[PDB]
Length: 71
Length: 96
Image 1 (tube, rainbow over the protein chains, first blue to last red):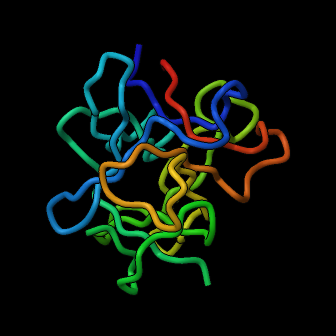
Image 2 (cartoon, chains in turn green, cyan):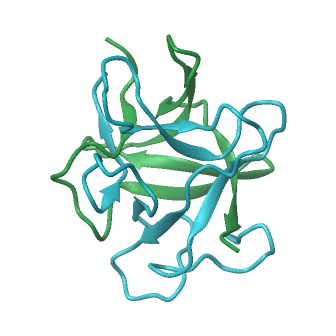
Image 3 (spheres, chains in turn orange, yellow):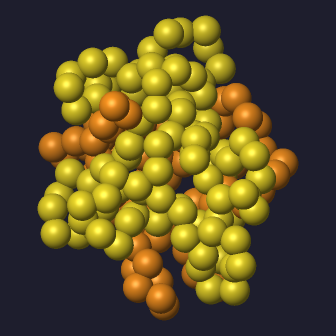
């Protein structure tokens, strides 16, 4: 087992709307996941076995981000 | 309030955005990679290079608002993604 992770591999999900939200968080924003049990869970980073910084559900340990407009 | 790096509201289903770390020295913007046994790059990761903005995304929120806000449920579409990925390539959560 390992922490649930963010993927694009599920062809069965909505192409408009979704279970994510953006919230304010210490000097930037965080991404959160509205879990099926009704608690929003922070997305954070976990370094995996091939040294990838994976975006995972990491309750209470958010990845703090900013959003740069393309162009 | 939710704004982009130039202080403008973020567009709903419009402009593309890069999702970038605030802290330096710890990886670049979010992209896709093969993880473990994957033979198609399906896993959201930050780019190994701090210089990289990663891949562009489009936000998709169901309300008809021109701009997204904090606390609003939305989907995240990765606008440039591997030919092997399902299209449109939408973030979701998976076990493992």
